[PDB]
Image (cartoon, rainbow over all chains, first blue to last red; front, side, top):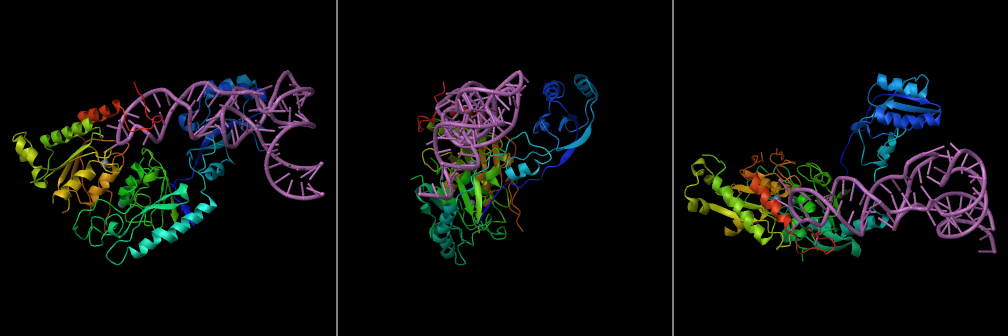
Length: 279
Length: 177
RNA sequence: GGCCGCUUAGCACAGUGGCAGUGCACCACUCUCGUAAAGUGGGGGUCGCGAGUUCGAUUCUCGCAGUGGCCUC
Ligand SMILES: [Zn+2]
Ligand SMILES: [Zn+2]
């Protein structure tokens, strides 16, 4: 059961606009250039397509996000040599970029100038079974043996997809985080600020692994990781590139893929990568 | 007592980026000074030997030689501080704003304060994205001021790509004039 | 044999009677954690092919060349 993690967004809304009806094609062909010269589309209103046919017949939209201009409409009438009637319509104010289904969802009222968004590959049928085998083989058993009450219970594995999803390196017992220490436990377990920190923790079980493959930077590998990496392991995954991340049980207290801030979706960062839940 | 920026500490931090620039590592240098040493009484440039001996730990961007692509300056000096020996209450002065990684590690170690001279938008932990006071517990946070000696901090970093790389794929390297 | 679909730049795929497009890319350019990344702009096309229709066809009409799915042998 893979649940793809995507940045939440709001559905688009509609703002008023003014349209008209067009009977002959050549008049509309001239009207395209006439409107381009007279009333160019606003930068926020360039996400639409002027060409449109009535459901019952051709009806043409003229003004976006407001009423028509008087002089522009008069010149349009003079070009048509006939009176122009106006019927109110509505145009979208929010631009979608990630969902093809949402992109089509409002296509009934009007199409979008921006084409169908590039649909990410929906993995494959056999790679799901490979993920299940790796879970039942490596990451989950560690989270079973790694934790007695004293060690935290987080395990992360750098899997190589090219060789049939084989474990290149797996974090062990001597790599995990102690419960008593509070330096490591802020990210993953709640209320770690209550207890003082006996030691200094620099490497979590997601950064120990990424520093054992240098033997470019893990570019193009994959990382099954049980509990969801914190904000530090998020930069572990973003400076050291990684194609996909599969966290099983999310961290509500602090996490760079879930609760705190979805790091992989941040625009200014170089390497954007996909994250799939697997419960 | 309190903590204030001290000029000589930032001079040491910025002169700890030129040495790493000669080595060819990205010019980011960090200086961990003693917690009760950043006091106003030490603001003056007097006693340069004593001031530069009070410096507890210094680090540079050792990622080129090490091979660990996840070891900036901040992650090195803290190791040195650990090696010479704690809750990292020492103040940390760096030339570029800590990346999200460093801003998370310093949060986890309860750093008292982290000054930086320049703001790096591509990877910035106290700039575009804020881990200064993001964590909510239940009281875990640090502070960071705007910028000191930014012109040098950007000149040293621009002098990096003007000279080319070395380890690179012949196709993927840039033969800039 | 039959039937259904399909052919568009180096590649992968839209799209429609009147401007010929979009992702990867042969490449070029701009920058603050190598600039081995990411944004940005340019050029890249016989839209099987032929005949017909149309002021005008990649589109519409027919046939032919090709591939693919099922069926028949
Ligand atoms: Zn972590
Ligand atoms: Zn950093």
